[PDB]
Image (cartoon, helix red, strand yellow):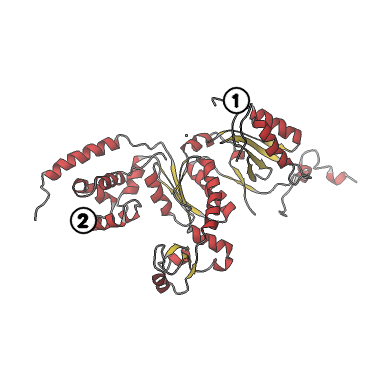
Amino acid sequence: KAQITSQQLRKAQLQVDRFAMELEQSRNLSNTIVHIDMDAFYAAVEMRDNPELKDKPIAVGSMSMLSTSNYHARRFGVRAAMPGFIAKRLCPQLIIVPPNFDKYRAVSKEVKEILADYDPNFMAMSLDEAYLNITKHLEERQNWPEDKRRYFIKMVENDNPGKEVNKLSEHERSISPLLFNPQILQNSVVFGTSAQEVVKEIRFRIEQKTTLTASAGIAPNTMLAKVCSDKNKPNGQYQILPNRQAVMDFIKDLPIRKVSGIGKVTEKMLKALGIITCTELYQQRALLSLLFSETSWHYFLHISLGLGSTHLGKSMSVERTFSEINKAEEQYSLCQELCSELAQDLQLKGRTVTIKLKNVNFEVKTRASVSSVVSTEIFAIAKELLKTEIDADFPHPLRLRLMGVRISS
C-alpha cells in the first residue's frame, strides 16, 4: 500500500500553518454572541398544556420516530430521532404525544418577540433555538439605570406596604399617638449590566411569558456559543470570557462529539484515525488537509482554534423612563415631545409606529399599527395607540414609568 510521505505531509503543514497564522492574527473577541436553546421545547409545551404529563417520561412524535424528549425520559436514554420501539424498550411507561406545530410556532413567536428586544437581527435557527449578538445591546445597557433593567416578577392580592409608611417619617411619628391611591406596588426584579445578567434577563422574561425554561451560552463567537449553552443544560447558562486563554482552555480536549457542526459520518471517519478531542484535531491538521474535503478541514482548523462566526442593519426608536405619570395630559404631551425626538430623520415620516409602555409594577406592553400608508406622522399614530391604552380599564388611569415609540416598516 502507498503512504503519505514524511515529506509531502510537511508541505501540507506549511500550507496549513500559513492559514492557521492568518487566522490567529484576525480573531475577534470583541463580540458577545449568545445561543439560546429552549429546554426540550415541544415536550415542555405539551407538559404545560396538559399538567398530567409534568411528572412523567414523555416524548413528542409517534412510534415510527421520536422528535423531542422531556428530561425525565432522557434519563432513560430516550432521544429525538429514535424509533419508538427502542424508546419503549428503554422506557416502558414513555408517553408518546403527537406533534402539534401550530402550538409550538405560537410559543416560539412569543420567545422571538423577546429575543428581538436584545438583537433585532438575531438568527432563529428553528423554533427552539437562536443566536443573538448582544454586543450592541451591551454597549448601551452599560449606561442604563435600574428602571430600564427592572421587570415585573410573577408572584394580585399581596400584602405590600403603601403610603401609610409615611407615619414613620420624622413629622408623623410622634404625633400618631397624639391624634384623637395607596401607592402599593407589585414586586419586580432587576438584572445587572454584564453579559451573564443580560442573558439571565432574557431567560427570566421567557419563563415568565411562556412558563418554559431555556439554556444558553455566551462566547466570543457563534460556534463556541452553541457548545456553551449545552454545558449547564436544563435551565443553566455558561460563558467563556473574551480572552484567548479561556477560549483555548475550553477547547482543550473538548470531545469532538460535543462539537455540533461535524457530521456523524465525519465523526465516524475521525474516530477511525483515532481522533476524538479537538486538540488531536489540531495536532493532525496536516494529515487532515490531505484526507478530508477542503470544507471539512477548514472547519476542523477553526474548531481547533476556537474560532467561529463573530457576526450573524427595522427600527429607529426613542424611550424615556420616569417616576410615575398617570395624568393623561402629561402622557400625551410626552408622546408628542417623544415623536418629535424622532428628529433622527436621514429617512414626520414612515410606516409601522409601534408603542412601548411599562406600568408602575414594571409590566411590559407593546402595541403597534401592521401599518399605515402614504400621502400628500408619528404622533397621529402614537396618540391613537396611546389613547386606546388610557381607555383600557378605562375607569382606572394608566400608571407609567416608561414610554417609547419605534418606527418599523
Q: Helix, strand, or loop for circle 2? A: loop
Q: Position of residue 139 (x, y in %)?
A: 49, 34
Q: Which label sits on residue 101?
A: none
Q: Amino acid at mark 1?
A: Ala
- The crowd level at tag 1 (other Cα within 10 Å; few <14, some 14-19, many 20+) is few
The residue sitting at 72% across, 38% down in the picture is 387
Q: Amino acid at mark 2?
A: Leu
Q: Residue furthest right?
A: 180
Residue 310: name its quadrant: top left
The residue sitting at 45% across, 67% down in the picture is 62
State the separation of the CA atoms marked 1 and 2: 63 Å
Q: Position of residue 256 (x, y in %)?
A: 30, 54
The mark that comes first in sequence, 1 or 2, is 2
**Residue that badge 2 annotates:** 273
Please tell me whether residue 42 is drawn above or below residue 373 in the rendered image.
Answer: below
The residue sitting at 76% across, 40% down in the picture is 169
The residue sitting at 50% across, 37% down in the picture is 137
Quadrant containing the C terminus is top right
**Residue that badge 1 annotates:** 343
In this view, the mark in front (1 or 2): 1
Q: Position of residue 264 (x, y in %)?
A: 31, 57
Quadrant containing the N terminus is bottom left
Residue 398: name its quadrant: top right
- The crowd level at tag 2 (other Cα within 10 Å; few <14, some 14-19, many 20+) is few
